[PDB]
Structures are given as C-alpha cells and as structure tokens.
Length: 59
Length: 114
Length: 65
Ligand SMILES: [Zn+2]
Image (cartoon, rainbow over all chains, first blue to last red; front, top):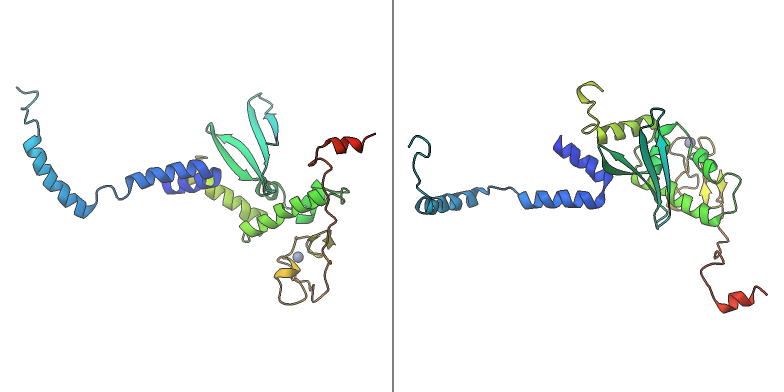
C-alpha cells in the first residue's frame, strides 16, 4: 500500500515524487547488517558512555 | 504561463478548482486536488476516461471546422500521438478506468469493496 | 482518414501509427485491420507560418501606415 501510494504519487508529481524518493534514499536499508555488527561494537562503547543512571522510578 | 481555471461547484456549493496547463511540449496536464493535496493527470486520459470515443471524435471536438490551424493541428497531433506513445496498452476506456482505479485505490479509500 | 498531418483509422477513427513507422504499405489500424501505405500516403505537409507576433519592431510599425 505505501508502495502503491508511491505509484499514485508518481503519477501526480515529478518533483514531489523526487522528494519522497529522496526520503527513501535517506533510509536506505537503514540498519546495515555488517554495519549492524560494527554498531554493536559501538554499543559496547555506549555501554561505557551510557549514563548508568539507576532504576529511575523504583528508587 | 497559459492555463485555464474553472471552479466547478457541486449543487451543495462545495467547490473543486480544476486547472488546465499547456506544456511547451504541446502536452496538456490537468491539476486537481484530493485530500487537499494536489494531483496532476494528462488530459487525454480524463478524456478517454469520460466517454468511449474515437481519436477522431476528440480531434473533431477540439479543432472541428478549424482545419486551418497548423499550429493547433500540430500541437494536437503531439498530444494524441504522445498519448499513443506513453500508453499503447490503454486500448479501451474500461482499461483506462482500471488504470485510474489502480493508481488511486490507495487514497480513495474504496478498496476491500470497490 | 488523413487530415493535414494526422491520419485516422478509416474504419475505427484511431490516429493510427505513422506510415513512417511501418514496413509494409498498409498502415494497419490498432483497432481495425486496414491497409495503407500498402495504400499510398497523405504526402503529409503543412504550410506552417509565424503568428506575426514574434518580431516586434519599428519596421513592423512601418507595415502599419
Ligand atoms: Zn481501426
């Protein structure tokens, strides 16, 4: 349905279609998988960075 | 720059503005608005969509007795021949309607029924 | 039918494919089966002209008096 929506968009506007397509470009696959692994490593870095704040509410 | 604007209003007085645009290419595109977003369609599509007709009926509809407008003869040949270029497969009006339903089905909220 | 530089299907009225894009003579209709250039051709020509507007000048005014 969104893709189909895209088709409707394609008929309506060349320019607007271009903008939406650009949005798709921005997304891309989003989480890359190899990238995902590297990111996981980054997450470890985050662990160090992380604001090890507490239970938040129970405390 | 040239274009036509007709503000069609239904009996209930709700309005719908319709615009025609002359492209430099001779192409004419039709502007309208749905869910208050704008949408453009080639006019030859809305023509073949309104009534089953021949190409000669539309040509005769526009220029008619005006057979002397080389300017119009050629622009209108660009229009009809150009449609034949884009959509060689829209052979009849029903198929055209299927193309419009297929391209607006996501937004006209008629689906699982129409 | 041929008019000006348009040629319509004689049987169906479709503006059939230009004799130029055909290998036979009879431009066949995409709605009908008629022959064509198999039957000759509408020696397609148009005497196209300027609108007598593109060329403003004092000399154009010299055509006005
Ligand atoms: Zn035919």
